[PDB]
Structure formats: C-alpha cells, structure tokens
Image (cartoon, rainbow, N blue to C red; front, top):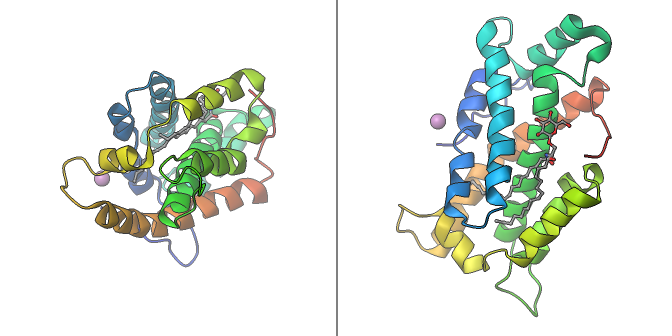
Length: 203
Ligand SMILES: CCCCCCCC/C=C\CCCCCCCC(=O)N[C@@H](CO[C@@H]1O[C@H](CO)[C@@H](O)[C@H](O)[C@H]1O)[C@H](O)/C=C/CCCCCCCCCCCCC
Ligand code: NI
C-alpha cells in the first residue's frame, strides 16, 4: 500500500503515518552489510518513540502537528530537543534521504562511467538530507557504506523480493510510492521550519 494522500490543509494523521513508515525498516534486512544494522535501529527507534508518545493519548496526538504543539507546551525550554519532536526531527531526515535516493534512481540519474553503481544517487541523497548534521566520525560511516554499496541491479532486485517483477516494473511501483511519500515529508519539513523546531547540531 501507498501512504495516505495529503489533505488540503496538510494536517498529517499520526497513526496512519507511523503505520506506513513502519514498513520501511524491514527492507534493511535485505542488505547484508553491517552498517544497515545501526541504520535500521536508528529509523525504527525513532518510529518507536513517536508511536510511544502517540499511544499515550491518540486523540490529543491525532496529527503530527499536534505532537509538536503539545510537546512544546509540555516541555518548555527543553523543546524541541525532546520527545517525539526530536525523534521525528531525525526520522524526517532519514525519510528524506530515502526519498531523494529513490527518486534519483527512478529518474535515471547515474555516473555514465559507472552506470550500475548507486554511488551518485546515495551521495546526492546524503548531501541533501543528512550531511549537514553529521560530524566527521558519522560521515565516515557514510563513506564506508558507499564503498560497499550494492550494484544498482542487485539493489533493485532486493527492493522487489517476493514480487517477481521486472526492474522496470519495480521502478514504476517506486515512482507511485514516492508521490504521497514526498508530499508528506515536504509538509513535515515545513512544519519544523514554521515552528522554528529545526535544530542544526551535528552528531
Ligand atoms: C520503497 C521503500 C524503499 C526502502 C529503501 C531504503 C534504502 C535506504 C538506505 C539508507 C537509509 C539511510 C537513513 C539513515 C538515517 C540516519 C539519521 C541520523 O543521521 N541519525 C544520527 C543521529 O541519531 C539521532 O540522535 C538523536 C540525538 O542526537 C536521537 O534523539 C535520535 O533518536 C537519533 O536518531 C545517527 O548518529 C546516525 C546513524 C547512522 C547514519 C548513517 C549515514 C548514512 C548511511 C549510508 C546510506 C547508504 C545507502 C546505500 C543504499 C543501500
Ligand atoms: Ni501498512
């Protein structure tokens, strides 16, 4: 299934969002390299934390905007470096990395001298989504992941394990997934900017 479409007023229901993005971390089990373990843990850990907050009062935390706004009231000067707000601040970055990476691949972006690597696509996604927030030690993790990254064809076979679809059919399904996914992430970014909740610290 696809993510829910964005409503006209751009308020994103928490429950459906968490349920949908909860399907993303299992993909990492298809990628054998040791770095995918802490990557999966990071993404899943943030999902878990936002879910834990949501579950304390689903009515009050019905939308992601509710989460930020209510946490701001709950935590005073500790906000936004607190709670589900912090978890979602980092989740959105992981989700944008995925967005940019997959979009790049689907649009045929490549290094003409290495057309079956995915380095250029991962580098674009990293620069757009994560690099500004990573100190050198974490950047080394990215660099090592790049070196060991699967070939494009292998990667796409993993995305479509279970489906028996062609590479081109796999890309078409990703393009459709990307529609509501991209729109939703863009709203989450806007929300953090509007609330002055984007933090710029490096890890
Ligand atoms: C259709 C479905 C498609 C699925 C396909 C998925 C393919 C995706 C591949 C990789 C996704 C990578 C996402 C990584 C997100 C990392 C977020 C991050 O920077 N989290 C930080 C901060 O952590 C935060 O610290 C905070 C406190 O300061 C805490 O409060 C937070 O809870 C905590 O999250 C953490 O320090 C870093 C974790 C790992 C960084 C990995 C760097 C890049 C990975 C290499 C990618 C190459 C891909 C090649 C293709 C296979
Ligand atoms: Ni689902």
